[PDB]
Image (tube, rainbow, N blue to C red; front, side, top):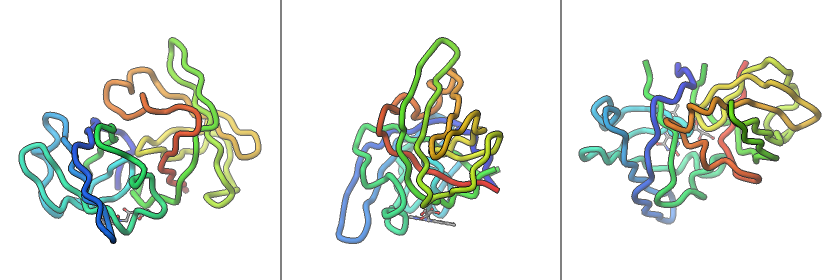
Length: 175
Ligand SMILES: Cc1cc2nc3c(=O)[nH]c(=O)nc-3n(C[C@H](O)[C@H](O)[C@H](O)CO)c2cc1C
């Protein structure tokens, strides 16, 4: 099982799209490409993907089975991704959700996400949830909008700098 603790972030460098899937070539951060190889199953934005090819710090994943309930087909070259290598999150993304709002501040970012009933209707505060590979506790909830707090230090190792109103994220429902 995964911790939902992002070890570092990669940058999508290449994306070859074909009729069935898309081959994403992700440039990994120093130290992470040495910990994986072909057949390695890891978490990219919290989604279980299998390394299909690797050369230096360029890691490739064929993204297909996940294309329909994930955010991958909407990412482009240059985008940052959260990365986690195995040793809680299973890596099976339930679906996609949008950032309803986001309030930055000294401490960190209070991000509001509108969770559709299609993903889960039985959410309670204090529960954990995975957003793009980051496991966080639901600090607050009102109907379908949940509130999660992001520590500012995350900007150094995660993709969170891309969160804005209406930005789509991978959601994994826990427990
Ligand atoms: C071991 C394992 C490997 C997987 N590899 C891929 C993959 O290479 N490409 C993909 O699109 N989906 C893959 N999936 C499915 C995806 O990670 C995710 O769980 C769901 O597709 C989200 O709807 C994999 C799932 C597991 C359990």
